[PDB]
Amino acid sequence: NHNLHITEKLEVLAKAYSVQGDKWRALGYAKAINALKSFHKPVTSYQEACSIPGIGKRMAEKIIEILESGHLRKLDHISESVPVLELFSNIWGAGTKTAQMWYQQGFRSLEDIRSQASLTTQQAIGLKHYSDFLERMPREEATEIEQTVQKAAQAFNSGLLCVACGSYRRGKATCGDVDVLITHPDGRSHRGIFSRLLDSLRQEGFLTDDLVKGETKYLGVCRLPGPGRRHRRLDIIVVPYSEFACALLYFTGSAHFNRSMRALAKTKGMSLSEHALSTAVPGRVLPTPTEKDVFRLLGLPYREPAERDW
DNA sequence: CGGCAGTACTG
DNA sequence: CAGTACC
DNA sequence: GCCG
Ligand SMILES: [Mg+2]
Ligand SMILES: [Mg+2]
Ligand code: NA
Ligand code: NA
Image (cartoon, rainbow, N blue to C red; front, side, top):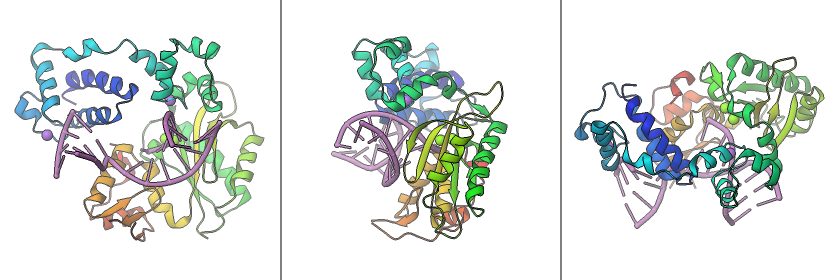
């Protein structure tokens, strides 16, 4: 990354737009930052800046300004509210609209939120684990969490397949949470397990709080036994076997890789979601028994998970 | 001008 | 429904 | 914000 003198400054703008709710401008900044972080050379021309995909006129100029003067004028005019909005929206279950409302109501600290804000069930859990949920775990801990869920699932039914995806499957040393995907080859026996499986995981004291408990996806909080353990975010998603390849691909990510893959599909008159690869104009679901089939039907060479870490 | 993803979940 | 979250 |  020969341009972190640029990307540091842009990252500040990106987050300011994100926490103020301008998600599209925030997306554009994010794309340009990612492009800047994988070019070979240091940029050093407005015509060089225009060179790279994801960088246009307005952002070329900003590189041209940090070009010469060494900083970016726009940074000095970011609203004083941004760090507080960032603080509030790092509560799980609070996004930009809730953060801006709390700010308008005069709240400025998590002590204000704790003492005086009306919190949803999810946000109260978010607040209780504010520090824990900002911490990444070693991938070795992610393995223990997966094997905990797997053990509990394979007790009620031997055939259940359980795979940790996200950054874990992409090979990262750190993980922000553990994303566990469960299916069954019989195509049948995957339904209705949650009641049994979550009650089991509660039997241990392993599951500590539930954030979402739907028919198909569970999001909550777990903690392994012993001293020195932190609470960790856990997602468990159950899918029919026919959709396993697309779900594996979606939940393995990364999010920018999936975004790149949806765009490529659209250029071919298809669509790609966590459930299926389809034709589109809805369209026809194409058969994808393996991740390799998704790439092949998109005319792409297969990429192992570790090379999807975009 | 307008897409840049679709869906599951909560209340 | 709006808002938030999953990658 | 970018790009078609
Ligand atoms: Mg994850
Ligand atoms: Mg997750
Ligand atoms: Na460009
Ligand atoms: Na949040």
